[PDB]
Image (spheres, coloured by chain):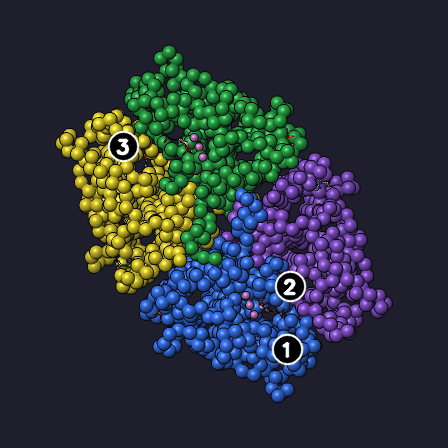
Chain colours: A blue, B purple, C yellow, D green
Amino acid sequence: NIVTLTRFVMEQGRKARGTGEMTQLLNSLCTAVKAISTAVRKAGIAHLYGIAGKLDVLSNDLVINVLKSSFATCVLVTEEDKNAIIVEPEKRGKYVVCFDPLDGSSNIDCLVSIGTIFGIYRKNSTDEPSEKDALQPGRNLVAAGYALYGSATMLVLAMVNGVNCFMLDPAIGEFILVDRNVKIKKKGSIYSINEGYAKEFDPAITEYIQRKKFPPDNSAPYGARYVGSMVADVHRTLVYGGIFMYPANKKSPKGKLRLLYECNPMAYVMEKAGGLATTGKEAVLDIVPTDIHQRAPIILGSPEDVTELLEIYQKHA
Amino acid sequence: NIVTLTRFVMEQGRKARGTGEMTQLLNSLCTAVKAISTAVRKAGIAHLYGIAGKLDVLSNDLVINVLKSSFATCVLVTEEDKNAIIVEPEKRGKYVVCFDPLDGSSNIDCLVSIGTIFGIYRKNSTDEPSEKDALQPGRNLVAAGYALYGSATMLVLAMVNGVNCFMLDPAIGEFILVDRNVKIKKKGSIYSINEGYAKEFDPAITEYIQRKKFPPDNSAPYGARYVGSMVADVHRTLVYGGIFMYPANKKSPKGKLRLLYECNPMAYVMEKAGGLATTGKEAVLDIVPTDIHQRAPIILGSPEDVTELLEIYQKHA
Amino acid sequence: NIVTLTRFVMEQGRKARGTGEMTQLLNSLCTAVKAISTAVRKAGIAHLYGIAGKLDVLSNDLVINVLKSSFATCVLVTEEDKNAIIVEPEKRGKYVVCFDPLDGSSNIDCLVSIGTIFGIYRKNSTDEPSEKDALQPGRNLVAAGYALYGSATMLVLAMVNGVNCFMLDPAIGEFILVDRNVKIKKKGSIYSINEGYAKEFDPAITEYIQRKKFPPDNSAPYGARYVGSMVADVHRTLVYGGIFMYPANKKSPKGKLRLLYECNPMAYVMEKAGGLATTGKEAVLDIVPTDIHQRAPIILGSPEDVTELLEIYQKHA
Amino acid sequence: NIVTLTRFVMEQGRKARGTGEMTQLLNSLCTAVKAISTAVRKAGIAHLYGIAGKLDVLSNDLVINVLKSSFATCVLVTEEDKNAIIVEPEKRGKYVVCFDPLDGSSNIDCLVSIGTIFGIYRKNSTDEPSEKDALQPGRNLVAAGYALYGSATMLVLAMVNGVNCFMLDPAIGEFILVDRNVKIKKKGSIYSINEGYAKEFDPAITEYIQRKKFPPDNSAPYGARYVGSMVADVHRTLVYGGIFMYPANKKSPKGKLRLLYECNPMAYVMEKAGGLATTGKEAVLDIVPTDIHQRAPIILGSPEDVTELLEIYQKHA
Ligand SMILES: Nc1ncnc2c1ncn2[C@@H]1O[C@H](COP(=O)(O)O)[C@@H](O)[C@H]1O
Ligand SMILES: Nc1ncnc2c1ncn2[C@@H]1O[C@H](COP(=O)(O)O)[C@@H](O)[C@H]1O
Ligand SMILES: Nc1ncnc2c1ncn2[C@@H]1O[C@H](COP(=O)(O)O)[C@@H](O)[C@H]1O
Ligand SMILES: Nc1ncnc2c1ncn2[C@@H]1O[C@H](COP(=O)(O)O)[C@@H](O)[C@H]1O
Ligand SMILES: O=P(O)(O)OC[C@@H]1O[C@H](COP(=O)(O)O)[C@@H](O)[C@@H]1O
Ligand SMILES: O=P(O)(O)OC[C@@H]1O[C@H](COP(=O)(O)O)[C@@H](O)[C@@H]1O
Ligand SMILES: O=P(O)(O)OC[C@@H]1O[C@H](COP(=O)(O)O)[C@@H](O)[C@@H]1O
Ligand SMILES: O=P(O)(O)OC[C@@H]1O[C@H](COP(=O)(O)O)[C@@H](O)[C@@H]1O
Ligand SMILES: [Tl+]
Ligand SMILES: [Tl+]
Ligand SMILES: [Tl+]
Ligand SMILES: [Tl+]
Ligand SMILES: [Tl+]
Ligand SMILES: [Tl+]
Ligand SMILES: [Tl+]
Ligand SMILES: [Tl+]
Ligand SMILES: [Tl+]
Ligand SMILES: [Tl+]
Ligand SMILES: [Tl+]
Ligand SMILES: [Tl+]
């Protein structure tokens, strides 16, 4: 007895008495992720080096095409696209999908873990689809998750029911359910942030970090880890517990991370796992977007760790 | 045209006029790395999950076995073994290999990049091979390098004539020379260290770090990155420039990283790439070891960055 | 735009307003076939040869387990099993599946193309499931098909709507629809039969062969091909046209091929493609089975070729 | 322990004391075979089918390119090329290679086993390399063998010291020695020939065939098998015993199969395996060719079977 993503999605669509439109969608995503995973591990590179005689771009095209061919979407928002993609009326479904095809594109050359981030909305309204359909607060997410191309490829899927992790057996091209109903640690022992911006941190952030390296109660300090790819850092947080942070600074007073296809998908996964995701002031999932490429600060992770910072945030208010 | 590791290695052994003993060794190694990469990527995991009909220990066995059968080694030192392994008189060769089968094994469950590290010495004290044979300064390395199981698998090989990077094409199980004679930037813009140990850093490290976040002449501060996997952090240093540091601290008064199978191979690769690798007080490669599992502090990366920290070390002494 | 087996099955289940029980079934079969294909191409053989220190049986277990875990079947009949497998009431569905996990097992050692054969029945009755549910004339098949592990792996699926061929892209573990609504040639130019039994053929068969090598109308003779694996011979017939024959002789007066899991699945595929499948006397699909391992003679292929023999059969009646 | 083609080849070159030139050649060949196997198995086909972003010609290019780059060849003869290819003075070596990149190309669309055939001669007439250099009797072969892309990929290598079979483990892209010093059964029980040419067979062939179906002393008749792919039929002959025949007929008065890249390599493998390979009148290996694309009749297989047919040939003359 083994559960595959294909089996799982189908049983879940069945319990929910769906028309089967969203199952077609989740199955198209699984296929797109397997195709990207293969391109990322460099299968076929020899041909490129003349054996017989871009990666973000290939990833964008794969997701966009595999999604359109699902006949389940009406609007697609990608980090690589200035405007939202409105689906041809022939292949139009009722879902709006926001995604980042290959996050951590800067790390590609250094071979660091990279990933794909997606969020699915049910179109709410009754008129010609447009960007406006994508502009829904994260709280309205039907499903969200990510695929991490690291030492192994894993798909983490979060829906109203919970968070489940699927490992890719590359030998048979099938995702195996390896961890179900995942809940994050109440309090972790690792903090993640680019301290190279110390000079730009607000006093609350500055204070938290200080408390982590030099514990006022003389407890053990927190270990530091900052991979440089959100999916890798967040995935480690989900699994090992701790806190990830990318607050505003000179690097945009609005933070660097995008709201629709990065912050929201990850906040949704986080909340479903039993942790928190805040901007320091408000819950990420409650922000009403104004633009499809709107950035937003984010702090996420174990509840006890995110609350501790939230307090320091209040103190300096 | 297309250059494969196999062709490159043979061609080099020919120019060198070797008896083909080292070529067999390097060919065995390459085979062991493709086997580990496959296990690491979780090929066949569906069988553990009951479709019907560890990873560090498995890696150790692969390396040990594939190397013994090469008939080119007499002494083996693994991070996984307390004692040095002495090869059977029947399979003995003239080479001594020091290796870390799967480095970054804490990052396994979090799916972060991990790797294999190897250093190769030639037994010169023709006596019954013993532990003593491995106790040579890194300055005596014949060959050294590593395999990084990241977003893609890469094998970095360093020898007297240079450093060359080989990318694995998993479709045909062949390593392709993607980069020839690799040389690191003189000065980088990323520092890598576990700042969670800030409370235990010597004044030289402490000063250098603060100088990176708050530059005297108001220049751009360095970005921070610390994956937590030496092979991954060092590969980023090699490819993009910067400095990696794992200094001595209370928990590790002599550092954490081992001399023979971690510090030395990375120091050797760094030097051949045109960079520096220091203890803070002396060059890693000149240290004559006393214990096979001896630890050593290490700082490596671009020459201009490593020098700057070396000056601060001189200033506080 | 590309159609995958997963997409295809889902859209077909949707058009048919099914509960989704048969889709779960066809999806479990696709997974089983990918797992068998991988075992057949010998991935992981190195471990068997001690790199770090039955095939029909593995195939039986894979199909049986993957099928039971679909929760869509009540009775399974396998060539490798003396008795029919009655599903645990926990995982009991309404379908009866007859299959040959790995046909051409004798050819394994010689590396000749081998395959899997399956036929799906809807249980008809309302009582405790038993072998008796498998004993339905082939005419009652819901779906049937085969997977051929040859130079490439292909799944041919036949349902009331028609016959469609899916090629396995082993890189992404997905079956791609490469040929839809396949129809066989009216008259082919190849005959397939083990002529080593010439001494045992009845006069009609003897006469047909003679007419093929020495055309009475002085037309070009037919080419001969007999791989030795039914799936390969039949698949070539479907694609290139011609006739395949395995009539009775000293090798059982009932022929060698089994009725439920070999003859029927292939006759069903054949008829749906627009060809014929006969025992010489009657249509294979109309035989009422008496035993689950009942053998039956079979002649199949292009209509004009099968009719020509049928006439010679009548002449000697 | 585990023996890989790479290790085996190097070890043999060492014992032979070669300059490593032939080893490079055999290593290049092995690389070309893994590349063809992958293309043959349809890895990446989903890209032709619009997931968004020949086979014989491709095989030809792979072989030609991978061989030229080995710097070990001066003349190449392909079934795909009218003229013999003369390697650039810059990449020239001392070896001449005669090959059939993808044999059985008619069986491609039917997914039947196909393969690559190669014969290697040493240029002895040290003159500007020309077509003349390839025109050597097979008796002068340095090495010969084939790659069979069947249910699994296998590489059969024959040299002065014997025939060895290597199975490809596609997971790690390594060929494993599965069978050492292969020797064919003295007498088999399967005959292989296209009986659709019965109307054009000489009396010797005609008599031998009828003697196989109707044995004088009532013994068991031989089974018939004719895949239609030489590499596949000959591999079965090699592994299981028997006889393969492609005699001269009206359509092919001198036979169909080519001498240099089909008959010779298979004749060489047969002789080293302890079998016979005849034209009916003379040994295939002793024929001194006049044309690079010269055809020749061929009969090979177990010694006892081939002799029996040779006697019948003597009787009718
Ligand atoms: N595979 C699924 N898993 C969980 N819920 C689903 C699935 N498919 C559909 N649903 C649910 O039923 C609603 C409508 O489904 P649908 O008719 O497929 O568009 C969805 O938006 C979810 O609430
Ligand atoms: N493939 C090779 N590449 C570069 N140098 C080699 C190679 N093989 C052997 N050598 C060198 O020649 C020495 C003796 O080689 P060997 O006879 O193979 O033991 C080595 O220790 C190196 O100095
Ligand atoms: N994927 C499918 N493709 C074609 N027909 C299907 C599919 N699934 C179900 N059906 C049909 O609907 C009937 C009952 O389906 P089910 O409720 O899934 O058991 C089947 O027996 C077929 O007639
Ligand atoms: N790997 C090998 N295995 C067996 N014999 C070899 C090998 N390499 C070279 N030889 C032999 O030694 C001769 C010259 O080799 P070479 O110097 O490599 O050109 C060959 O033609 C064969 O006789
Ligand atoms: O994909 P991008 O645009 O290259 O950025 C990735 C993001 O970049 C962040 C890191 O940026 P900093 O260097 O500023 O820390 C990660 O947290 C996210 O993956
Ligand atoms: O394989 P190990 O014993 O788990 O250690 C890996 C090493 O551990 C260092 C990081 O450890 P810290 O958490 O102490 O920084 C890395 O740079 C090296 O990969
Ligand atoms: O799987 P099996 O039991 O080995 O047999 C396979 C069948 O065996 C038939 C051939 O048998 P003959 O040798 O008698 O022709 C093929 O047509 C079928 O694949
Ligand atoms: O590659 P080709 O030109 O298609 O030919 C393959 C050969 O063709 C012979 C069979 O041809 P016949 O149909 O004439 O028997 C085989 O034994 C050899 O593989
Ligand atoms: Tl991106
Ligand atoms: Tl991004
Ligand atoms: Tl971003
Ligand atoms: Tl380790
Ligand atoms: Tl380590
Ligand atoms: Tl260590
Ligand atoms: Tl069987
Ligand atoms: Tl069978
Ligand atoms: Tl059978
Ligand atoms: Tl050909
Ligand atoms: Tl050919
Ligand atoms: Tl030919």
- The amino acid type found where label 3 is placed reads Lys
- Residues flagged by tags 3 and 1 on a common chain: no
- Residues flagged by tags 1 and 2 on a common chain: no
Q: Nearer the viewer, mark 1 or mark 2?
A: 1
Subunit of label 1: A
Between the residue at mark 3 and the residue at mark 1, the CA separation in whole angstroms equals 84 Å
Q: Secondary structure at mark 2?
A: loop
List the residue tagged with mark 1: A249
Identify which residue is drawn at 77% across, 40% down.
B127
List the residue tagged with mark 3: C251
- The amino acid type found where label 1 is placed reads Asn
Subunit of label 3: C
Please tell me in which quarter of the rendered image ligand 8 is found: top left
Q: Nearer the viewer, mark 3 or mark 1?
A: 1
Q: Nearer the viewer, residue B142 or B62?
A: B142
> Residue A131, how many percent across, how many down?
44, 74
The residue at label 2 has a CB less than 8 Å from ligand 6: yes
Report whether residue C92 is seen: no
Subunit of label 2: B
The residue at label 3 has a CB less than 8 Å from ligand 7: yes
Identify which residue is drawn at 45% across, 22% down.
D277
List the residue tagged with mark 2: B228
> Residue B45, how many percent across, how many down?
49, 55
Q: Is residue B49 left or right of residue C277?
A: right
Q: Are the two marked residues, 1 and 2, in contact with CB atoms closer than 8 angstroms? A: no
